[PDB]
Length: 306
Ligand SMILES: O[C@H]1[C@H](O)[C@@H](O)[C@H](O)[C@@H](O)[C@H]1O
Image 1 (cartoon, helix red, strand yellow):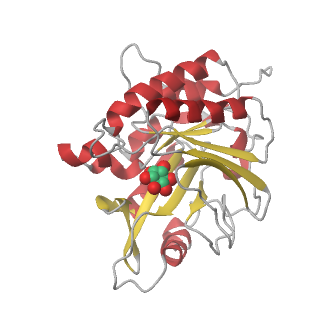
Image 2: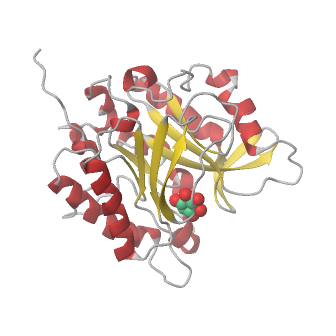
């Protein structure tokens, strides 16, 4: 049972699977574990574990949001709020992790979350491409293959870019083309990505009240359960914005939704889920089903003789 050993669960799958076909736990605003201020954490904090611990808990999709604070520097951010570290820290942690667990792959979403400092001359995509993706420091770290729909075998030991920066000149990863990903605001939507090779289906209704959010998540989970198309990629965000008045913290919200969705997954048996992106990945509450574990265990192991 895969969720008992979350450190190396991908290494247990058939490596011929497309990443799209693997049920992957992701963490929303992954780098926000740095916040400790109780007032701002109500709304700005979405994770309590650091990157390495999230990886050890089985998280393989990371939602990194950035701001260029100088021409050679991307700082990790929740909108205007600095999260106390730069992109190099996540890349070093993933590198160390993928070294220790060389048959896992990590998907890293990269998005601009705030306006650059006015002294910055370069676009966010130029900075990411020149100072990180092409940095010789990260030489064997990213997926650099030409397969628009790569398999686990092809991406073992690497970070596969998931591009939310807009058009890019990077040629590997999801949305790595000059058009990027057209991302609809506060919605469930579909858009063709990678010069038309893949159909990307997103639930990102980040302003929904609880009942409407649960239905949007279940709706996309139901679509996935009956869809074995390899060229369809599902990204299903359980996270919502905390609200300044409608005070129910991201943590309170996650304590409702994560177990509710975990229980539905568990009842559906082993069936395709897509990539489910959660707040407080790995945070357990006694007597509640755990969303990360149930995502992991929803992957079907075909039984071969040894
Ligand atoms: O605040 C939201 C939220 O974090 C979403 O999941 C992200 O896709 C949106 O673009 C962002 O505006």
